[PDB]
Length: 275
Ligand SMILES: NC(=O)c1ccc[n+]([C@@H]2O[C@H](COP(=O)([O-])OP(=O)(O)OC[C@H]3O[C@@H](n4cnc5c(N)ncnc54)[C@H](OP(=O)(O)O)[C@@H]3O)[C@@H](O)[C@H]2O)c1
Ligand SMILES: CC(C)(C)n1nc(-c2cccc(O)c2)c2c(N)ncnc21
Ligand SMILES: CC(C)(C)n1nc(-c2cccc(O)c2)c2c(N)ncnc21
Ligand SMILES: N[C@@H](CCC(=O)N[C@@H](CS)C(=O)NCC(=O)O)C(=O)O
Image: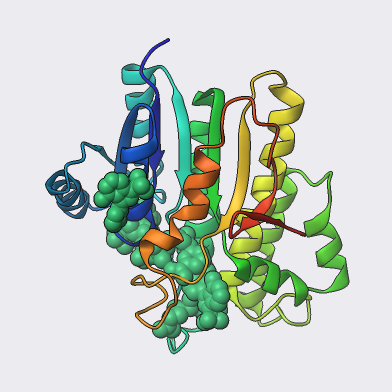
């Protein structure tokens, strides 16, 4: 059939850029680097061109629904869909940030959970058979899960939870921080960690829906942690290079055709972790 296409969100720097670079070399088709800032995105494309690579570019800010929709329309028009989607874009307040916690919660949740969700709402319908979806979560999601109340752990581990139930819970965390009741209500103290619970559970729900609604289509969807990577997020003391951080996401993006799994798993260092 037609030309295959892979796309990475937050592709202008850090792990996203390393993922783009690797897909340029390893993905059999076009690779679209996306970035919210057009200047930074184009600069990244130029960087890869100087390395001998040929990524395409399209603007994308996962917090602007019009930007997501424009990208959706582009993919439909130019490719008739999408083969690989890497939801890499994410943010985190610094450990030392004095920003009031409730603002940290609202802002981090807005991008990491709601932005990622919005991208999936518009782009999952475009995924072609044998496609792969990779959601970059964090081992912090596993850590944060342990600090939730037993009641919340049960909900987050549920095999029957719906996307709309999860949306309610994520917004509940944010609202609870605003009311000064998040601890009493069973939430952990890491806003970032809770947003990544959101990403992990969203992955589990979307994998279920793919298996239930698109049987036979051979689509695999997983959450992952890239490990601790030297980027503008984690800082210079981290143990992995962006190259090393890209290995697990690229692995999940390029699972060979007809492969049975992993599917709906949380993967770290190419290995399935218990949720
Ligand atoms: N140790 C680690 O570094 C580590 C570990 C586990 C998980 N992660 C996860 O790995 C992913 C990549 O992080 P990183 O370490 O590479 O961080 P980074 O260097 O800060 O890069 C983050 C990328 O996401 C983009 N982004 C942020 N908000 C966006 C938005 N609203 N719309 C579109 N793009 C947006 C950023 O664009 P700008 O350049 O415009 O800001 C940048 O391209 C994140 O999801 C992070 O949570 C990182
Ligand atoms: C073997 C892969 C495809 C992973 N790879 N990686 C790299 C590579 C090497 C150093 C840094 C980097 O980001 C990527 C590479 C290269 N330069 N030439 C040919 N193949 C390369
Ligand atoms: C700060 C420590 C070293 C605890 N850290 N931070 C992170 C980390 C840093 C930035 C983002 C993230 O999701 C996690 C991390 C990791 N992924 N794996 C192991 N250790 C990690
Ligand atoms: N108070 C924040 C802490 C978030 C956090 O742990 N940030 C880490 C990455 S996940 C970070 O920015 N580390 C680098 C640094 O602080 O220099 C929250 O609750 O979300």
